[PDB]
Image (tube, rainbow, N blue to C red; front, side, top):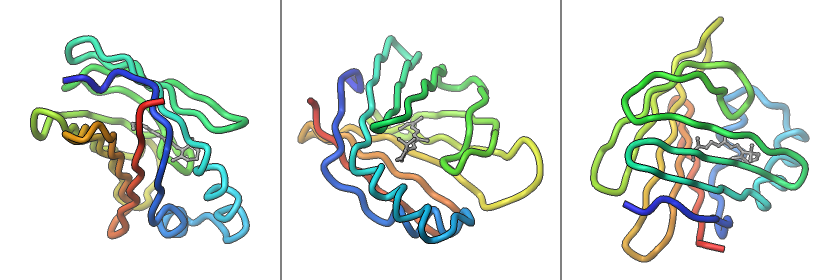
Length: 137
Ligand SMILES: *C\C=C(C)/C=C/C=C(C)/C=C/C1=C(C)CCCC1(C)C
């Protein structure tokens, strides 16, 4: 479908609770929550190949992958992982991650296009699910 677009966050839920699972201390969590209110996602999708640029006010990175082929990225708290994206439905993809070194919570993310034109991203650490909602800019 059409994940392609420039997406601006309109809602962020449970992000602090996710970072807490990930071991981030309280005051860095609060500043990161503030940073998540400026979270923007730029997506270019060509077939099952995705170019995704995620950014806040002072930081930007790119995540490029093809559905079904392993790649390397980082968890949201910054630890390197191996990742594999698969479709779950026409408009939703799920990414499973595996830490490259050491241990830690089981992390994953998802992206979904709703039939209202919203992008819904979730991020998971063990038990805790962060949900962020975007609209096209
Ligand atoms: C939606 C798909 C992918 C691959 C996105 C991954 C996004 C992140 C690891 C984003 C982290 C951020 C959050 C949620 C808010 C503060 C700072 C970032 C923008 C880096």
